[PDB]
Image (cartoon, rainbow over all chains, first blue to last red; front, side):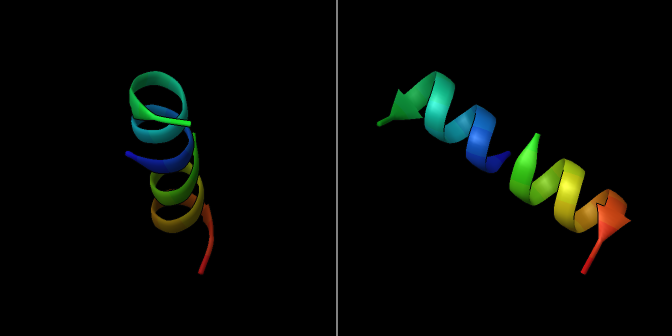
Length: 16
Length: 16
């Protein structure tokens, strides 16, 4: 979760 | 992975 990869920003799901 | 929770900074494992 958060900024990098997962749920959040960068990679996986969310944004970025 | 990264900043928030998981492997990286904030919560779970790594730092913060």
